[PDB]
Length: 4
Length: 302
Image (cartoon, rainbow over all chains, first blue to last red; front, top):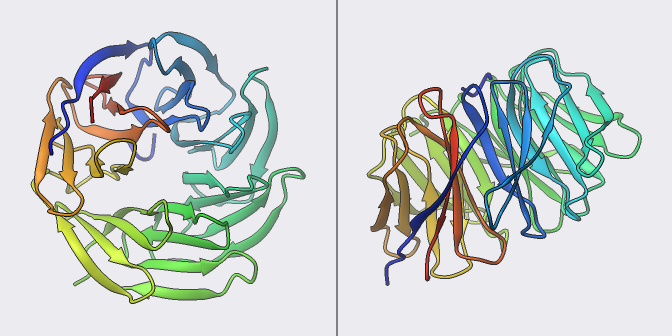
């Protein structure tokens, strides 16, 4: 991954 | 006056972008999570790969240590969190309840509760020993980008793309305060004394908030941050700094009091998504994205  | 961080180790091993770095409280290791579905443990002092922790079915956006450094928790797109035994490497519990990507996570200082934040916009509070969801908070009207407990575990701060930070009562679930312009908040955490909260927004700005007086005391700028939920840090071991990743590939260090940039760490070849400060030594670990895929360890005299 989300954050990526 | 100014720190002098210098490159010591580049740690390689993750095959996709690194999502977050966290030094264990006992100062010995560093844990990293990554889009490659893996948690990796490294030596804090030597930069040596210790082990890989796997089991998640999709990527991992966050990882956090328990207070005695015995446990990890990880937040995955597979809609779950996992509690890991750091020594055995094995998955102790799987926390199921979220209805979408799990994005952020943390233990309370006591480390018998876990807080999580999700793209289903809830903040959940889990019992570490049984694995049950004790509370679900409909916390935001946008995905939750950070959760954090305070020095005594009584408070939880959370932030969101909706532009608000919200402080919660761990025990009741009640919302205690809300900080408000209002650009997306990509990260928040309490200061170590728990009196202020540090908030990152997607308008290239870190703000330091007096939590109780609900007002903004200091703002730090100069870095690039418009897309990613980048981790920010209080550095307390030497000089008192604000530390943070940046979308121009640098690590930024600010003087907490004067708001001036005191150092920029060059070396990464992609967005620095995550930085972390060592418990006792003047050491910063930084991690970068798909074009880099490495964690770097830097050390300073102050």
